[PDB]
Image: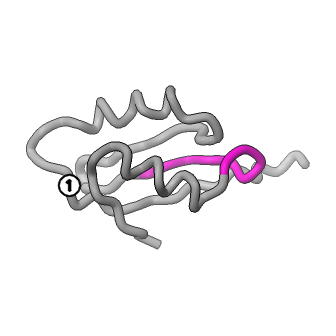
Amino acid sequence: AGHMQEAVVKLRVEGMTCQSCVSSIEGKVRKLQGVVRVKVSLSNQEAVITYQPYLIQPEDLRDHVNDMGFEAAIKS
C-alpha cells in the first residue's frame, strides 16, 4: 500500500525537568526496532513516538517508553 500505515503516538512527560534528557531520549530510537523515529517537544513538555504497525505494536512501544526512566501518559 502506497499510503503510510505508520502510526505515531504522543505521550505527556511528567518526569521532564530543567535538564535536557530530550537529547538522550532521542538516541533511544536507535535501539528501537519497530519504532521509526521519536520527536520530543521541550516547549510542549511532551514526547512523540513514531512507530509502525507492520513492525512493532503500540502497546509494546508503551513499555519501552518507561525504559527511559520517565513517566508518560496518553495525550490522545
**Colouring chosen for the image of the structure:** one colour
Residue furthest bottom as drawn: 76
Asked if 21 appears above or below 61 in the picture, the reply is above
The reply, left or right, for residue 14 in relation to residue 27 is left
Point 76% across, 53% down: residue: 5
The quadrant holding residue 25 is top left
Q: Position of residue 71 (x, y in %)?
A: 29, 58
Q: Which residues are magenta?
A: 48-56
Residue furthest left as drawn: 18
Asked if 72 appears above or below 65 in the picture, the reply is below
Asked if 49 appears above or below 58 in the picture, the reply is above
Point 29% across, 31% down: residue: 23
The quadrant holding residue 13 is bottom left
- Mark 1, secondary structure of its residue: loop
The reply, left or right, for residue 31 in relation to residue 40 is right
The quadrant holding residue 7 is bottom right
Q: Position of residue 48 (x, y in %)?
A: 44, 51
The reply, left or right, for residue 70 in relation to residue 35 is left
Q: Is residue 50 magenta?
A: yes
Point 46% across, 47% down: residue: 64
Work out whether residue 72 or residue 3 is closer to the camera in this orientation and state it. Answer: 72
How many residues crowd mark 1 within 10 Å: few (<14), some (14–19), many (20+)?
few
Q: Is residue 40 magenta?
A: no
Residue where numbered disc 1 is placed: 15
Residue furthest right as drawn: 1
Q: Position of residue 40 (x, y in %)?
A: 36, 45
Point 23% across, 37% down: residue: 21
Query: Which amino acid type is marked by label 1?
Result: Gly
